[PDB]
Image (tube, rainbow, N blue to C red):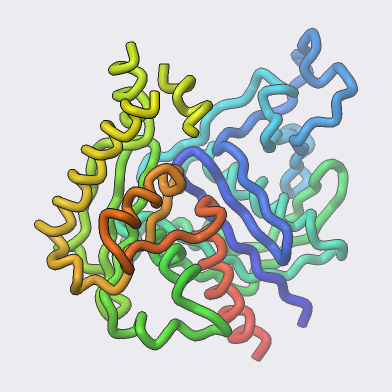
Length: 321
């Protein structure tokens, strides 16, 4: 058979996708092109990074998805992100356009695939997983910028999101590293609004040693912009040096202190993977805080997808058998 592996990560405010050597990261927003013509958007000739999607012959709804969405329409809206997003039109359409974008990267008309993705650890076994897998596991006709692709799904594999990250750094040639099978690892995710720690022991998540700090990069940059008496500004030009080190000094002390309280002796931990939009900002200081324990992957935004892709490859073999 001719089967491809689609890895998708429907996260916070961005959707990440990868197929073969092709990948994308686009805000979790969707639009629609309607005849209520604008003055410039969609009228001028600029070649924008946005595509048109027609699903199953429904010409009455031309969906708009891409990084330049708002440059071509005024219909752009954020997609549902609640725990019940699986039943909201917004998210369902986002899933179809994301699948469509990956399908467009395959030259042939008929695109057979397996889909590897993830979901919040807390819904990974509930009725949510059943509805998400139902959205994913089906055939569909998608026309991307006028090009029809017939998409057949031969299999779906869903894991807890932090697992994609762990797998990015603990798996090669279809096998997890020996150390990972009986080790203790934590995923330290510096998000925009929260900082999440997920701990795994012998490949299984330990809820008793996982936690969330309700402070993120937005809070960081805000707390800095204040002492300097506008975060958007600090974000642009990180190389206020004094303030930075002060805010970050406290952030790191708080995070590691919580680690020692909840996870344990930092020496019982085999690795702490630092991920999230804030990883690049704090990895350096963390590395000097404790030696030989923190690790970071390049392009942290794609870590989950690279991890899901490996599981997708294994699912692809199971199917080709």
